Amino acid sequence: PTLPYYQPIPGGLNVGMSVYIQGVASEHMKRFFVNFVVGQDPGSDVAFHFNPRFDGWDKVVFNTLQGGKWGSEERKRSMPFKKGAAFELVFIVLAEHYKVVVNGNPFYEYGHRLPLQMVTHLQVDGDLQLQSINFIGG
Ligand SMILES: O=S(=O)(O)O[C@H]1[C@@H](O)[C@@H](CO)O[C@@H](O[C@H]2[C@H](O)[C@@H](O)[C@H](O)O[C@@H]2CO)[C@@H]1O
């Protein structure tokens, strides 16, 4: 797959589904994001924005974009990616939250703010190369 990636999630999200992304963080990475998006029209809401950042104290930001407004960020001040390194990034969709697992290590649980059933698309962009994106347990 090529970037930017913005593709429908076959069948939409359901509890029990996993999204499995294999990629390589750029040697020159500043940020990348994975968005679970409600639609494909301009101005679409983002149910879940997952955003690793190397600018400053390395961290991952988690948020929702609704009605053109970013919500209150959740943040984890740990960086599970490494510049130039391949990663395995998994989102397990559960009733209460998205469970994020990186390279086998549980990383975060982001509580649903928009109903998960409204998500139609996965969008990925930023400073990485993608090897694959797979939807499991749909
Ligand atoms: O690429 S973007 O989606 O435009 O980047 C935005 C997102 O990463 C959101 C996620 O919350 O953050 C925005 O920046 C925030 C910044 O993290 C925060 O420290 C500051 O207080 O507010 C900014 C604007 O909401 C990104 O612009």
Image (spheres, rainbow, N blue to C red):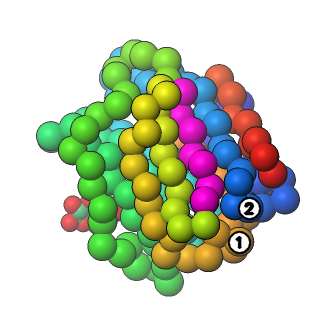
The quarter of the picture where residue 20 lies is top right
Number of numbered callouts drawn: 2
**Disc on the earlier residue, 2 or 1:** 2
- The residue indicated by pointer 1 is 117
Q: Is residue 99 visible?
A: yes
Above or below, 110 against 130 in this view is below
Q: Quadrant of the N terminus?
A: top right
From this viewpoint, which residue is outermost toward the left?
57
Cα distance in 3D space between marks 2 and 1 = 7 Å
* Kind of residue indicated by mark 2: Asn
Above or below, 64 against 9 in this view is below
At 69% from the left and 28% from the top, the residue drawn is 132
In magenta, the rendered stretch is 88-94
At 44% from the left and 60% from the top, the residue drawn is 110
Whether residues under marks 2 and 1 lie with C-beta atoms below 8 angstroms apart, the answer is yes
* Residue 74, label in figure: none
Q: Position of residue 136 (x, y in %)?
A: 76, 42
- The residue indicated by pointer 2 is 14
**Main SS of residues in magenta:** strand
- Is residue 62 left or right of 3 when viewed as pictured? left
Q: Is residue 32 visible?
A: no
Ligand 1 near label 1 (Cβ, under 8 Å)?
A: no
From this viewpoint, which residue is outermost toward the bottom?
67
The quarter of the picture where residue 55 lies is top left
